[PDB]
Each structure stands twice: as structure tokens, then as C-alpha cells.
Length: 279
Ligand SMILES: Cc1cc(-n2cc(S(=O)(=O)C3COC3)c3ccc(N[C@@H](C)c4ccc(F)cn4)nc32)n[nH]1
Image 1: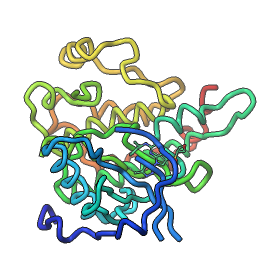
Image 2: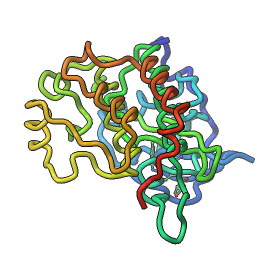
Image 3: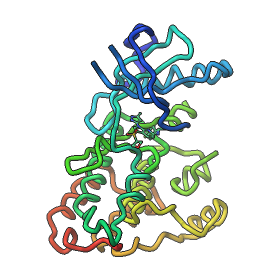
Image 4: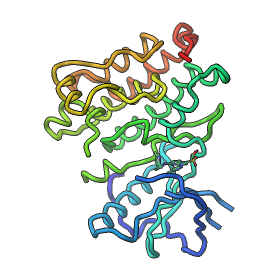
């Protein structure tokens, strides 16, 4: 279940059956298939031939995943311009914006709870376990690349963008372990490190990692052994998962099966889930 497919296996949706509504972001439109709501990621008609294969390849990989914590590919419109990849619409939006906007505030407190954060972490960890089990390295696990099905209770978090893994088939230094940015070595353990950073992102409620450091400051900091402090109010058991994710040797980092169990232990400890979030 690697790249045992080609363009011909993609579901071509006739262009006249696709409607573009409103723009959602960049780096994509809300759309309609005739009925059915979709997201449409577009390839600018103004682009190089390298861009075109990059677009095509991303569609192929996303079409081949089958996992509940990975955004679904509905289909494609590659034979008309601009080319489209049609993807599952995620009304909860990107994980970064969700955390920043649902931060408990005086007017709306207890908006989010620790357990809700644990569930997002589990969801994304579950998707990463599937990628690792299928020998796929994401290379860019980060809150900005995760999506939520809806805002309220019952939200599901899914990995929803694969641009960086597609590129090596600028660099997000603040999410990369030493062996990645020093050697260009990528393994399933480099995603583990990134998951630790994402974990820090979740429990900080959408803070930028290493908040006062530049990329080079981080690179020197991480190489010399420096690690982030716990997010405000972060339970110890959760921070320990982050710190085990940031072990210097990849071989000393947990795989995603182990991370999931550890998040679940966190999920069934009252001192963890009864910890109040900062407002
Ligand atoms: C593939 C997909 C995307 C998506 N989507 C749904 C909304 S939204 O629900 O309209 C939100 C507006 O306020 C509520 C949304 C907003 C921004 C966004 N950015 C794009 C660049 C993106 C792509 C991948 C990724 F992981 C993160 N972001 N994508 C949004 N659904 N499905």
C-alpha cells in the first residue's frame, strides 16, 4: 500500500458537476458536487511543470489513504483547468485557529477542557500510527496541518495537508528533530518528534513553539539539548509524553502505538483531566 497506483486510478469528477463557492485559505475553496459539500484544493493555472507533478502526486497519495483521522479524498477534476483535488469539508477548520479562538475567556469559560485536548491528541496520534504502520513519513506534523470536523463536542481531528511530504518525494525547523535538520534523515521517529511539538501546540492552546526564538536560535538551542518548558497548566504526565517525543536519539523516542497508550493513560487519570485550563 505504497505508490502502487497512477493517475488513472483517481476518481475523475466531471467539471460541470463541481461548484466553487467561497475561498477558505491558501498554501483552497469550499465547494459543491452535484447534494454534497466538498473542499476544493486548486492548482493555479499559472504554474511550472514541477508544480504540476507536485499537485498530481499529492492527489495520488491522499487518494490512497483510508483512515478516519485523515481527511478523505472525494475525487479529482484533473482533466480541466485549473485542476482540482476534492477533499472532505472540515467545518471545525484548522487546529491552530481553533485553539486560538476557543481559548477560555472571561465571557466564555470552560469552553474547552483538558479532556478535549487529549482527544485531539489521540485523534492525530491515531492518524500518525496509521501513517507509520503504512511506512509513510509526513515530515510536517503541525497544528496548522490538522483540521477539525466541527467546533463543538464530538469534533474529530484529522491530518489534512501533505504538502511537505509531497515536496521531498522553507523548512519547518521548529518542528524537526536534530537528525532531520542536520542530516536530512527522515524516519517514523522524525514524525514522533513533530508530534511532541504538536502536543506542545495543543496544550499551549495554539502558541507558536519556541515563542521568542528565531529558527537559528532554535537550531542551536535544540542541538545543545534545550527543550521547551511545559505549556501553562500542562499536567506532568502530558509534558512527559512531549519530552519523550523530543529524545535526542530517534531510537529513544516512542513509536505512535506507545504514544497513543500513554495519551490514553492520561485520558483515564483524574488529576490530568480535572486540571483547569488557563484563561
Ligand atoms: C482540506 C480541507 C480544508 C478544510 N477547511 C475547512 C475550513 S472552514 O471549516 O471553512 C473554517 C473557516 O472557519 C471555519 C477551512 C479553513 C481554512 C483552511 N485552510 C486550508 C489551507 C487547510 C488545508 C489543510 C489543512 F490541514 C488546514 N488548512 N481549510 C479549511 N476542510 N478540508
